[PDB]
Image 1 (spheres, helix red, strand yellow):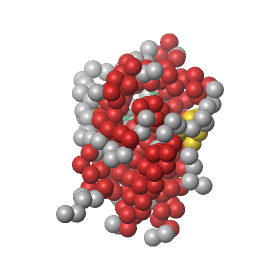
Image 2 (cartoon, helix red, strand yellow):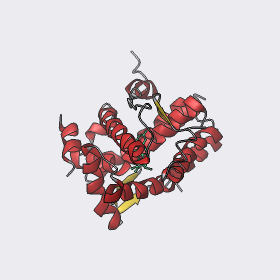
Image 3 (cartoon, helix red, strand yellow):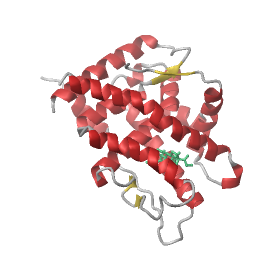
Length: 243
Length: 11
Ligand SMILES: C[C@@H]1C[C@H]2[C@@H]3CCC4=CC(=O)C=C[C@]4(C)[C@@]3(F)[C@@H](O)C[C@]2(C)[C@@]1(O)C(=O)CO
């Protein structure tokens, strides 16, 4: 027979790019822009729950574990994909949040935008610097989902460890499909994602609690952010680093 | 527990 490759499977469960429906006819405010991004983000996260579910192995975790991983890593998954789309669609020059919603120079210049957009372009330019391939990206994306765990560790740490084993192998296969040196670089990029995202989480928590700014969040994200917020205060959240 | 997320996982 010949089981289809795990790469080929990842390729087909990769979600299709969502659409913002952003109306560039009305005037650009920064509360408006951020509230849009959050709404779009809400949708991307739903799209990412579907993806995780179709993910060979993911389902064998305890439901607590699936929660924990999706809660702890959503912002990384989203920023990673964003970085990818910006890499493809504009070669890392502009944030391509959707095809109907790109960030240009007006709207990076809007209040609050420049800082946060700088950080997300950093992610983008890594893909540029390392000429990352689609297959490399897909495996790295799975490893991102599996990169943050409670300091307590997970319930079914058993299954957890074997899942990482698989996708680390998969990452290696992908490196090949496109040479010892490469795997180092990539696991270093995975490592450096924790820092690159920490800033985004910080600003996110700010716009979430700052009542004056009237940045709206979909109930999807709000529920996650509200749950995550005491856990980051306690600092009870462990990055898995390769180095 | 994030009710919508939990929900999406249990369907
Ligand atoms: C700087 C932060 C990080 C941002 C997120 C970065 C990752 C991401 C990628 C997308 O393609 C869609 C939305 C999200 C998931 C995001 F873009 C929005 O949600 C807005 C966001 C949280 C942020 O802009 C805010 O906190 C604004 O309130």
